[PDB]
Image (cartoon, rainbow over all chains, first blue to last red; front, side, top):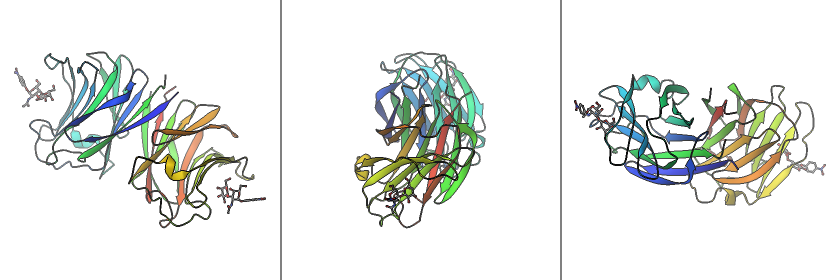
Length: 159
Length: 159
Ligand SMILES: CC(=O)N[C@H]1[C@@H](Oc2ccc([N+](=O)[O-])cc2)O[C@H](CO)[C@H](O)[C@@H]1O[C@@H]1O[C@H](CO)[C@H](O)[C@H](O)[C@H]1O
Ligand SMILES: CC(=O)N[C@H]1[C@@H](Oc2ccc([N+](=O)[O-])cc2)O[C@H](CO)[C@H](O)[C@@H]1O[C@@H]1O[C@H](CO)[C@H](O)[C@H](O)[C@H]1O
């Protein structure tokens, strides 16, 4: 049966999913703020991650204000960062909506479709495969482009 | 061709969907407040609706604090309200989450699965079929159990 799960992630923390995200499933991160004027990242201002049970970074989404870019990557638990995919113009992706933001990830099996608010920003071909069993939102209060608390909603059992 | 559409509905208004909601699709209403101490409804404190192209209420979700019940019903544009399905203990459905809430609707074709937060409250057998062309959130800035503006998110092209 289709299901909805809600998690509240504090900047810099992770949450274990009660229902893993697999092929055909959906995950959306919700921010109750949009701070496109925050200081520079070191180098990241904000990141959202989809973890496998073994700790692999299935999907790493990093937002860099000063570099004006959004990075999409993956990584094994004890391996090096893999091939980065970049998308310039950070502010442009959040256009049309101020004060809050949304990042959605459709798990399509061979790829992760990433949507910023209503705009699909990338069709990310997976570098690592696996069920998403954990999620994290990493940032500080000072330089995150999102609210200190980011709400994550998963839609599972869809296929 | 999955897609995400975002709408911000002010209490008492309707919004037209850019991408219709049909079998296999999902729509979630997000409230940035939870007012279980609001004045009595008249009889509704808050209603969320899915409308067909012809104005028919495909799904009418009515929250009644005083009556301590949630109504699920349908009706043709110029027809009478049909057979109500009801669920008691309103506050109980929102248990565990204070200050906000969400109501998700899964269009399963023959039924609408309504989920408040993570809790499935009803498997509503459709009284009227068709694609959802519009949505609405009806209430007053004084007795709604939700925030004045409710955000509606649709995930379409999932089937
Ligand atoms: C500080 C900074 O901008 N780091 C970038 C930079 O890091 C490197 C690393 C190695 C070399 N090199 O051997 O020539 C050059 C630059 O570029 C990297 C990509 O080439 C990364 O963008 C790195 O930042 C790291 O990115 C990963 C994701 O790929 C992750 O976000 C890390 O937290 C981040 O430090
Ligand atoms: C004020 C109130 O509690 N209205 C209820 C009530 O209305 C009726 C109507 C007819 C009869 N009757 O012929 O014996 C009794 C009560 O009960 C109705 C269901 O029987 C409705 O619940 C009505 O509220 C209306 O419900 C519809 C959805 O079904 C919609 O929410 C309307 O806005 C609401 O007024």
